[PDB]
Image: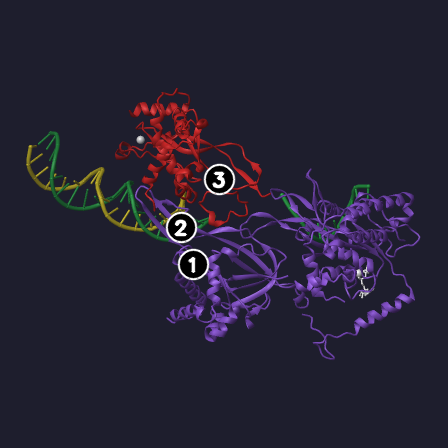
Chain colours: A purple, B red, C green, D yellow
DNA sequence: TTAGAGAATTGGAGAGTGTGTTTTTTTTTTTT
DNA sequence: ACACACTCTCCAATTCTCTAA
């Protein structure tokens, strides 16, 4: 009956006030926040008692129950009244697990009853619903009662229930072996862990791998009973922004996507898309769109696809899509039959999952127009209306669209106007904020530096790799860039009278010039949407400075950008 | 657990003694006036307000908020016991179902069949509304307040409350109160004369005697 | 002659056991 | 949890036989 000594070990481990008192402090915090689970770091346990630590990982169940009882006794010794508020306490684990860190592919039947640490990408969820643990019945005519664990009438207030949910984890597709589809596993979430993860999240789950029963065919289904769930995704920024020696926005734009050479204005516009504008609301109930949309058109081999694959790696909550490989149902939402409950419910599509994020559409000119009808409502209003599976609803799909396409006839024709080369409808072309045209002008002076840069890139080898190796199948630093952009997304700067005056006067001047100009010399007409674009771009530039005001410099930069985009051949 | 008899007397005391400084401060004892109207069949439902209870006994309010179903039954029985004291008048006969009850009284000379009133709670002003996502399993059995948009509603259907049967041979009647969403009906007479003689009389259900209530189903959705 | 008590055979009243149970992607012909 | 089909048992109703009113 050594488990009574094992519980005794855990209780004297938890009583660490004699040695710097970290865990007693954590338990005190748990009490103050009215909580009922604790998170223990396995490194500390391994340091204090090697035998107990190395036994815990290979006997998850029999050891964790002893640990839970030790915690219950310790909190009761601190405060019995608090200990009586909850039926039982729980403990979760963190740290380094060594050999027990696995994936949904490498996890096999020999891991049963070990503590395991699985990681992958979440693909689906069931709905939260209650489960019974103890039921009670009472008789008022006799003052009598009975109980059961898992005449008289049921006592819902003396009975007690707890929450239950199921989710599914999938292997990272980048790590799949050659020529095979990804594998997956089912995770069970219970009590205070429900709804801590949603589809598209990258998670790392700690739990115990276990069979479920099922005459018998001698065959079982295996599930991971979760024990903890984890997610993954100042002075430096202060002194850097305080310098004011140079236009910081130009330096950040120059440093964007170092592999790709040229295309200055495109990089500046993409940085404005990453920073975004700001929303505003009016007393009549109307509101102004804060997010930005961008379109790219051009010849073969001008790095259009690579810029999309870069933004997708350097922005939070970003999604890919290709014109030929996707459907309107897949873009918005699809009805699904739940196998846990049997019920019919909706499942999110690509543009819904990109809410408060970015969505990249490659090969945009190959979509059927019926899909573009779905994209129209999303890009204009940020909402999507659905009328299926007994639900009439207005879902949230607020996102910035970055899209790329190739011109009609494959190679752009100099002897035709922009509206002739571009294959899209004039209604749709009016929705994007900025439209860029890119061309492979075969100048030898430019080919010299381009070819040199490409060849420099192909001779590199990483410092952690040796002279002849080959990989298996399966300027500002990037880290600072991410942190600076992340802080800059809070500032919410405001207009100034001078910037407003400048924008108004300059817009009137631009309108007069456009009135003089002809469709043979412009991509699209200029209207109030131009003012909205100018305001968004000036706001974003002020945001990059972290200046609380929108200044004349921001407005001047914004108008120069749109001037280049609209009034160059 | 509490003695629900003591709690019944406390509830009676609240109904008998509470005045809200009511009728422009004239102290006319709102619930006493309501009991007069209920006794004279002027009114059907009675909404007891928990803010009124809080003036005298906040512990009672807390007792009600958890395991509300017990206190629903308790208040209903208290009101039924107090109703004759606020009666002074004889009411005119106006309903076929009550004509059967009148015949039953005339022939005699369960309470659920006679209990022609409804009792409901109006939530305490302390309790802010939850969203449909925050009503988790720790709230089972407890009084709650929720906010949302209606999506669908059914027509009004008759819901059975107590069934009334008649016996072909012995001329007696039998009753069966209903509580669960389903039930099973009776078949053969349980009265002592039929049973002792094993005479085999059958039971016929009477829609003219049994009691029904208006029932409707609805769905509500998040903003 | 008519009727009741003690012994033998048989019907059926009753219990126990075993078992069943609209909403999305892709192809093919013929209409345009 | 709630209905058919089947098997089986014990209690006491119906008749034979001997006897008294
Ligand atoms: N300026 C450049 N810097 C770096 N690589 C470049 C540059 N221009 C072209 N490339 C190369 O161009 C190749 C193709 O890039 P890609 O993004 O597919 O071009 P694209 O404009 O999208 N052409 P396409 O997809 O056929 O319409 C890549 O392998 C790059 O290495
Ligand atoms: Mg490409
Ligand atoms: Zn009867």
Q: Looking at the picture, tell me which residue is in the foreground, C5 or A30.
A: A30
Residue at coordinates 83% horizontally, 51% vertically from top-left?
Answer: A559
> Which residue is outermost to the bottom?
A467
Image height check: is A475 above or below A410?
A: below
Q: Earlier in the sequence, mark 2 or mark 1?
A: 1
Label 3 SS: loop
Q: State the CA–CA distance, disc 2 to disc 1.
A: 16 Å
Side of A525 where B172 appears, left or right: left
Return the chain for callout 2: A
Judged from the image, the quadrant occupied by ligand 3 is top left
| Tag 2 residue | A135
Side of A549 where A32 appears, left or right: left
**How many circles with numbers are drawn on the protein?**
3
Mark 2 and mark 1 residues within 8 Å of each other at the beta carbon: no
Q: Label 2 crowding class (10 Å Cα cut-off): few <14, some 14-19, many 20+? A: some
Q: State the CA–CA distance, disc 3 to disc 1.
A: 33 Å
Q: Ligand 3 closer than 8 Å to the CB at disc 3?
A: no
Image height check: is A137 above or below A178?
A: above
| Tag 3 residue | B125
- The spot of residue A422 in percent (x, y) is 85, 51
Label 2 SS: strand
- The spot of residue A396 in percent (x, y) is 66, 47
The answer to whether any part of residue A155 appears in the image is yes
Mark 2 and mark 3 residues within 8 Å of each other at the beta carbon: no
Q: State the CA–CA distance, disc 2 to disc 3.
A: 31 Å
**Circle nearer the viewer, 3 or 1:** 3
Is disc 1 on the same chain as disc 3? no
| Tag 1 residue | A88
């Amino acid at each position: 009956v050594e488990l009574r000594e094992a519980q005794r070990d855990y209780l004297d481990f938890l009583d660490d006030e004699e040695d710097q008192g970290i865990y007693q402090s954590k338990v005190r915090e748990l009490i103050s926040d009215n909580q009922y689970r604790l998170i223990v770091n396995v490194n500390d346990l391994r340091r204090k008692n090697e035998k107990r630590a190395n036994r815990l990982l290979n006997n998850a169940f029999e050891e964790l129950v002893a640990f839970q009882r030790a915690l219950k006794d310790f909190v009761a010794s601190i405060d019995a009244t608090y200990a009586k508020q909850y039926e039982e306490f729980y403990v979760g684990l963190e740290g380094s697990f060594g050999s027990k860190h696995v994936s949904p592919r490498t996890l096999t039947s020999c891991f049963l009853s070990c503590v395991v640490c699985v990681e992958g990408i979440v693909t689906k969820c069931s709905l939260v619903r209650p489960k019974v643990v103890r039921s009670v019945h009472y008789c008022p005519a006799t003052k009598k009662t009975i109980e059961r664990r898992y005449p008289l009438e049921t006592e819902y207030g003396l009975s007690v229930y707890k929450d239950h949910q199921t989710i599914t984890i999938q292997e990272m597709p980048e790590k799949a072996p050659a020529g095979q589809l990804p594998r997956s596993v089912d995770v069970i979430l219970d009590d205070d862990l429900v709804d801590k993860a949603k589809p598209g999240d990258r998670v790392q789950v700690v739990g115990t791998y276990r069979c479920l029963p099922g005459y018998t065919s001698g065959t079982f289904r295996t599930v991971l009973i979760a024990c903890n769930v984890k997610q993954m995704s100042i002075a430096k920024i202060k002194k850097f922004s305080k310098t004011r020696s140079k236009d910081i926005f130009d330096q950040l734009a120059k440093s964007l996507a170092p592999s790709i050479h040229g295309h200055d204005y495109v990089k500046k516009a993409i940085l404005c898309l990453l920073l975004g504008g700001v929303e505003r609301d009016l007393e009549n109930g109307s509101h102004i769109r804060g997010d930005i949309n961008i379109l790219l058109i051009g010849d073969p081999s001008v790095a259009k696809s690579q810029l999309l694959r870069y933004v997708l790696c350097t922005a939070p909550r970003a999604i890919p899509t290709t014109g030929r490989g996707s459907s309107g149902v897949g873009l918005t939402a699809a009805v699904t039959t739940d196998q846990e409950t049997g019920e019919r419910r909706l499942e999110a599509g690509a543009m819904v999952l990109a809410d408060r994020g970015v969505v990249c559409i490659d090969e945009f000119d190959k979509m059927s127009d019926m899909d573009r009808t779905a994209i129209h409502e999303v890009m204009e209003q940020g909402r999507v209306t659905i009328a299926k599976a007994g639900i009439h609803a207005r879902l949230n799909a607020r996102c910035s669209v970055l899209a790329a396409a190739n011109p009609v006839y494959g190679r752009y024709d100099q002897y035709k106007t922009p509206m002739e080369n571009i294959g899209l409808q004039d209604s749709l072309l009016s929705r994007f904020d900025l439209l860029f045209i890119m061309l492979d002008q075969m100048d030898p002076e430019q080919d010299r530096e381009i070819s040199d840069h490409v060849l420099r890139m192909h001779r590199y080898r990483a410092p952690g790799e040796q002279d002849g190796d080959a990989m298996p199948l399966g300027m500002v630093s990037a880290a600072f860039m991410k942190k600076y952009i992340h802080v800059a997304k809070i500032i919410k700067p405001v207009l100034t009278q001078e910037s407003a005056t400048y924008i108004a006067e300059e817009y009137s001047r631009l309108r007069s010039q456009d009135s003089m100009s002809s469709d043979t010399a412009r991509t699209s007409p200029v209207t109030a949407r131009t003012l909205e674009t100018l305001i968004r771009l000036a706001t974003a530039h002020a945001k990059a400075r972290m200046s609380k005001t929108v200044d004349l410099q921001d407005a001047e930069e914004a108008v120069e950008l749109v001037q280049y985009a609209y009034f160059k051949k | 657990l509490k003695d629900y008899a003591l709690e019944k007397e406390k509830v009676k005391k609240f109904l008998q003694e509470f005045y809200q400084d009511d009728e422009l401060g004239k102290k006319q004892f709102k619930y006493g006036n309501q009991l007069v109207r209920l006794a004279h069949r002027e009114q059907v439902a009675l909404y007891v307000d928990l803010d009124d209870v809080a003036e005298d006994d906040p512990e009672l309010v807390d007792s009600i908020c958890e395991n509300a179903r017990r206190y629903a039954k308790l208040f209903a029985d208290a009101v039924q016991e107090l109703l004759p004291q606020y009666k002074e008048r004889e009411v005119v006969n106006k309903d076929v179902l009550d004509v059967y009850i009148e015949h039953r009284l005339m022939m005699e000379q369960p309470a659920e069949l006679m209990r022609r009133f409804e009792l409901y709670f109006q939530g305490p002003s302390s309790n802010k509304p939850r969203v449909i996502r925050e009503v988790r399993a720790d709230s089972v059995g407890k009084l709650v307040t929720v906010r949302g948009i209606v999506t669908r509603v059914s027509e009004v259907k008759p819901k059975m409350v107590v069934a009334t049967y008649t016996c072909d041979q012995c001329g007696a009647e039998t009753y069966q109160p209903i509580q669960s969403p389903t039930f099973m009906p009776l078949i053969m007479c349980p009265s002592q004369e039929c049973q002792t003689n094993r005479s085999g009389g059958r039971l016929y259900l009477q829609t003219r005697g049994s009691r029904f209530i208006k029932f409707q189903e609805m769905k509500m959705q998040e903003h």
